[PDB]
Amino acid sequence: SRRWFHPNITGVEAENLLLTRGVDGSFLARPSKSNPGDFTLSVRRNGAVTHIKIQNTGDYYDLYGGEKFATLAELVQYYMEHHGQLKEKNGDVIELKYPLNCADPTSERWFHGHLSGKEAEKLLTEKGKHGSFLVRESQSHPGDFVLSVRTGDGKSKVTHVMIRCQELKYDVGGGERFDSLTDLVEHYKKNPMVETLGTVLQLKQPLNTTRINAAEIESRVRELSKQGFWEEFETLQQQECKLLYSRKEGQRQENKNKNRYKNILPFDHTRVVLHDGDVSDYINANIIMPEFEPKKSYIATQGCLQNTVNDFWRMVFQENSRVIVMTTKEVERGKSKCVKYWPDEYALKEYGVMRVRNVKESAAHDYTLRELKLSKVGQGNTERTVWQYHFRTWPDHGVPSDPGGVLDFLEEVHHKQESIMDAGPVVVHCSAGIGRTGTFIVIDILIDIIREKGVDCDIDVPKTIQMVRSQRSGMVQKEAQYRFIYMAVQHYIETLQR
Image (tube, rainbow, N blue to C red; front, side):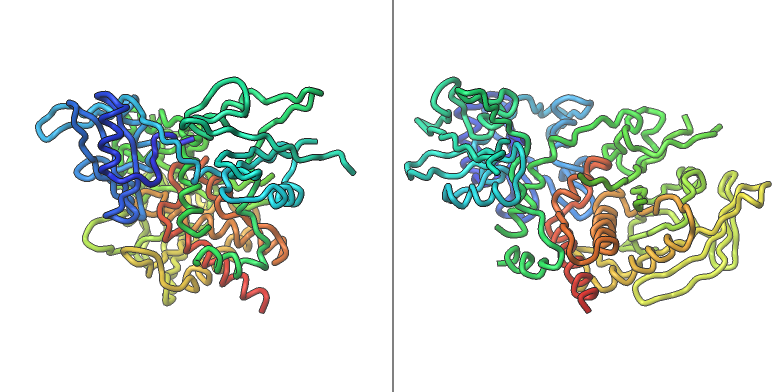
């Protein structure tokens, strides 16, 4: 439902498109062909198109020479409405007014392309349930399309609705003619077709094409590497307009300086709220609570700023967290991604009301473990041990070339968490708390399913990531992190089968 994203036009085609069926204020987004992994926002201005470059780093999105953002959709939403203002060479505003929509269905979850009617029915027979649907290119073979829906031994059935494609518009056989399959699908999702005898063709969810058996990940990763990692990742990105929840508190003027990046904010419905303060209730952090159709939870947060060290420790104590995961080096590559928030070994420091004492550091190859004792000043007895696992060897660009460093790291983290009864959520941070942080948390979630349920269980990487992204914006930034997640689960899986 991210309709203004054109998954493969050329920037030249994007110009003529904006100049012919757009007006001043029209815009679209497309992936950059010249800068793989980055994006171009094309905008019509004074009857001319300008192209704004957006870099997707492993930590955020970077409007070149401007602000950083968690997702494309949050970036567009910012300028279309909430605050924003995007300015010219001098100081004249470039206004984003009118999304120019794309008709390409190839990235949509429900779209399957070349597919027979008997293979679709088998797919819906097998993995589907009530309301599961898919859209394939026409059997009876014209150049039309077929909507296959599963409704309802004979209690269930698959119904095939044909979709006419006539002079660049789509329909079933009566009613409205739509500019794209996506508009058609969204329309008849909201207004279900009814059969002559009353059967309601509800469209409740596209047929799941991404869930696999965990024991079978080696073959799926093979298929994905030959359908493929990039297409699967783009299909997930195409779902980000469903995740534009409000971030008002982080947007309050009093909280602006508590964000390392002003537009990378915690969702209100999941943010960590600091109690018993002096505002003083705000930290850029979200509970991540995995849910699927007794568990381990996480706090995803940014790296401390100088003025937020004390609230970070307020958070750790309040939430009874006993394990921190730091995914960024102590000295990175010149610019601070996190202010040091822990004492040196055998030292101790007060942080506001909070006292912490570094009891011991164990140096491993890929990480340092710091044993810290946190307590409220004046009230030793509120004291508890917090174990800081500082991951040291994550590369500065890209992901690690082997995930064995991360897996051993997370194994230690998991056993420590398990050793403390009723420990609160594991704290995880990186620079903005979404990219690297998102990668570590998703990996640990999937590995946890396999630890409980064993190797004969169902895992679904895109849906797990979408579930995480509804609790903090832009979790898991790039395709290389996405592949890393599959790779990490694979090597974990071929260690239990051993």
